[PDB]
View (cartoon, helix red, strand yellow):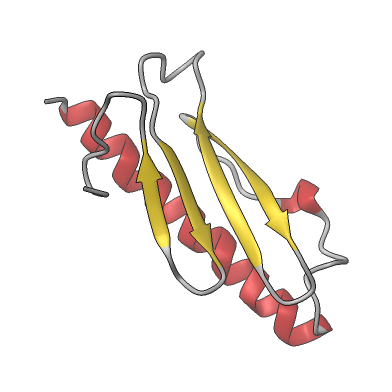
Length: 98
């Protein structure tokens, strides 16, 4: 196993949760996710965070590993507005998500 993968995967959990909280506040202010400026997502040194799905009442955030700083990591981590967090890799377990 790898201490560094465990740390980095734990940290991207936090990055995703912070982004989800920001969007939960935006929804209470605006009543939709459709107008949210995707440029405002908080990033991580080791994972690129995007909105893979956006609809009026739901979203999915996705963290894809950054190969410049995190080469060898294949786990992609997702978090939706219902609070479901999940990770899957390419023949690679995702510590903290398995």
